[PDB]
Structures are given as structure tokens and as C-alpha cells.
Length: 291
Length: 291
Figure 1 (cartoon, each protein chain N blue to C red):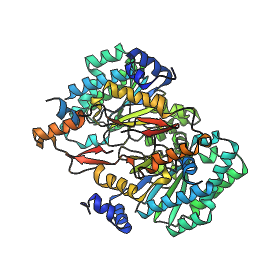
Figure 2 (tube, rainbow over the protein chains, first blue to last red):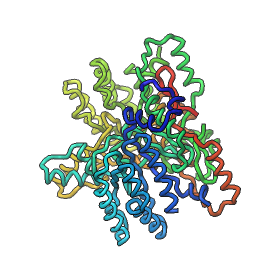
Figure 3 (tube, rainbow over the protein chains, first blue to last red):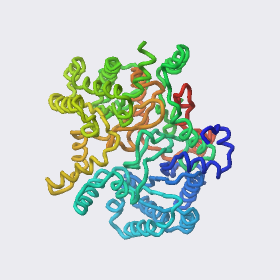
Figure 4 (spheres, rainbow over the protein chains, first blue to last red):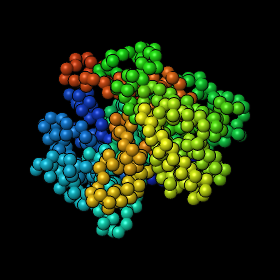
């Protein structure tokens, strides 16, 4: 339970890992679907392919015991692409709430789906967009009885400030008092969600689109390859690091360590004095982390 | 200007780097003062030493052209230490607003100092605490005429939600309309501050305490050694990566690349399929990033 080795963890059967996760966490994980286009021009040679991969990873995440997955899918730069790109995107959005296989996926894995972000005001003031919003509203309610997992799709969910302000102003007008943090979170995500226990990005070290759910306890990981490339081994090593390594116990007692130990520890830092993770190099316009 | 090499950037004189930064950014940088205790039991053998190091790094940051530094200094776990630890902390806080040398530092470098977080309600409901709050209020106003730099100290600045809600409710009651994002930020930090262009942490890959100032454009870096260990070389390599490498231009045009290029790029990922940054190992209870 508390003393499983990485090797065993890596050898254990799926159901076993899931049980460990259900107990130790991560309860909430952020997994944006990024680098999609790149993955497309490298493995397939769109909207339809991206989805099968999204479904694969989501399936994987939930089958490993993770209760809630927060997945940013569309951020600001969107409205700045061509008209066709926007249509392709709005179609992808429509697929998350309309496609046959993913709907089966939600039902098969008892997944309640929610959407967050500024999509209701930002989405194109057109028909196709009003359809996406209606679709989003419908799915959220129709998957309402599923209780095994929670899936939150981020659509323009990069800055919740103005949204929190307005949500708070209305709540106080109708309730007489300001909302609690819990109510603020329910208001934005549509349901209460604990802080994120980990964020798995890729490439450039950066996080985004999970307003109010971030804390110093959100373990950060950045794969070298794009989101859809996520393998089993990689996921388990990430899981193992967060569950067993990030918060090691008992904490360290310096005063109890020998003068040599402190010395060995000091060298772990001074041996390579200028070492830093996050600096990279560029190849074909693509940034890659060094060291 | 736009085509300075890393080597030149690393060889350039301080004033030169500062000029490049003033023009290209980072305009806002987050630098929490973490791992202080650890650095103490490794280099000095407290409250007074931590400050000289804090001053050194802050001085360094501002002298490199960075306009605003956001520095989380005290988070939640604080109130959970012994009574003496809390007193030592409240004394450190008092030093930021009272000590002779740092006050000279603010004046010498024309630094306006601001405090953010839940410290006004969370700080001990004692005398020494009411003194810190008064001290914080006084400093903020007394450094009000400095315009070269802005320093924001985070004291319990881990979750601004409830604070934004209440600030928004009052603002609407008095103004008749909800505040804008800009006003919400001014309300929380006491002045408007642009989103953070970078966050330099250390050890475990994680970010914290800069509510509302985070975006996908906040470049993340994690040194291997604790905050106070920050060297010149490390800072410039971080700066160089963010200014020149993170957002390379022109963007990549896949369709224009040869079949071999795409192939070489594909191998950069498939050669080492399970590579991920953020997984570590533990030594003496201390986590260290691998790879």
C-alpha cells in the first residue's frame, strides 16, 4: 500500500494501479490536448483523428483510477486563426457533445461531462456556435447521473477573474451574502472540484487554463512528445512520482544528519551550480527542453 | 537587438542586458524565496541572513531590467509551525518593511513595494501582527513615489477567489457595475500588474502564489538548487531562453519542410518515446528532478 516499489507499480495490473490511485490520488488531473496539429503532421499521413486520441487518453486516465480530468481544449489564439480553422474547431467541439463513440464512452465509463470557460460570450455569435452552447448544456445535464468520473472541458477557460466577479455579484444580490470558495468553484466549473493534484503538459514548461484549481501541491510534468503520444509507462512513472515521491515522509531532519550527509547533499547542488530545468533549444521552430 | 547570440548575451555587460530586457521583457517575473531553511543548514554554519540573500536576488532581478518582481514569501503551512517559527516569520515580515538596508535598497533602486494575500485576516490576531499590517500599509504608501520598479510580496497569497468575490461585491455596490479585470487586479495587488512573463522556482516542478497573473505565456523554470543559490549565469540563461527561445519566430510551416526534416523531427520524439520532465528521485527526503 504505502511501500510499493516503482518496479512493482510498473508491473502491477491496471485494476491494481487504479485501486492505489483511488486511495492515494491524484484525485484531480489536468491534461490539456495540445500539440494536436503537430501530432497530425507526424503520425497521420483531422477532427476525427484528434478525437480517437482524445478518447484513448481520457479512457486511460479514468481507467487508472483518476476521478476527475480537467482538459483545456480551446484557448484564446483560436478566434485568431482563419475562418475555416474556427469552423473545424467548432465542429470538434460539437463532436465532444454529439459523436456516437464518445457518447458511448461517457456512458460506458459513467462520465459526467462539464464545460468551463468564456465560451458562452466568446464563441462566434453565429448559429453553429449557439448550437455548440446548446449541445454543451444538454450533455452536462444528460450525463448528470454518471458518478464514476468527471470530465471538465476548457473552452476559453484562461482567465476566470471577470467571471468570478460577476458570478459573485449576482450571488450576493440573490443570497444576501458573498459566495464561499466552494460555491465560486461550483459556479465556474458547474460543480465542486478539488484543487488539481497534477498537470501533465508537453514541450515548453508552462501551465494554463485551470483557473482556481491550482496550488503549490499541483505536481507539474512536461513530456517531450505531444499529448496524444502519452504511453502507459510514462503515465505510471508520472503517477508514481506524484504519489510516492513528491511528498516524501517523514520530512527531512537536518539536525539529525551526519556532517558527511549534509556535505553530500551540499555537493548535490554545488557540483553543478548553474543547473536549471526549463531552458531549451530550438529545432525547426520547435522548442525542446535541455539537460 | 533581435539577433543576439546566447554567447554574446552571456558576455554582454549588465547595463546592456538590462536594456534588452526593458525592450523585450520579461516585464513581470515571479521569484518566490523558497528553500531558505535548507540553504541555511548548508551555507551558513537566520532571519538576518535570509534577508541579505533576498536583497541580493531582488537587486539582481531589478538590475537586469525586470520592472516587476512578484515574490511569494509566506504561504499557508506557516500558521502550522511552532509558535516560535511564527514569531520568527512575523519578524522577517517586519524586516521587509522596517530594516535599514532594505529600506535603502528600495530608495536606491526606486522600488515601490506592495503586499498581497490574505495576511490582513490570516495574520495572528495579536499585536505584533497588527504591527506588520500597519508596517505593510505604511511602506506601500511611503514607496509610492518610486517608479523604476515594483515589488509585490506575497503573504498568504495562495487563493484569491474569496477575495475577488468580496472585492467585486463591494465595487459593484459603490460603483453600480462590476469591476473590470484590470480593476480586479488593482484591487488584489493594490496596483495594476501585467500577467507574469516567467516563474523561477526550484526543486519540485510546481508553481504557487501569483493569483490572476498566470497564463500559458508564463515561462516556467526550476533550478536544481534553492532560490538564494541563483547565479548570474543561470539568470541570463533563463532570460535568454524566455526572450529568444520560448516564442521563436517565424512559427513553423510543416507543409514547407522536406520529408526528411519531418522524419528527423519525428525521431526527436520517437527515439526516446517515454521521456518526461518532472519525475524525480529522493535523497535524504529531498526530491531531485531526473533526466
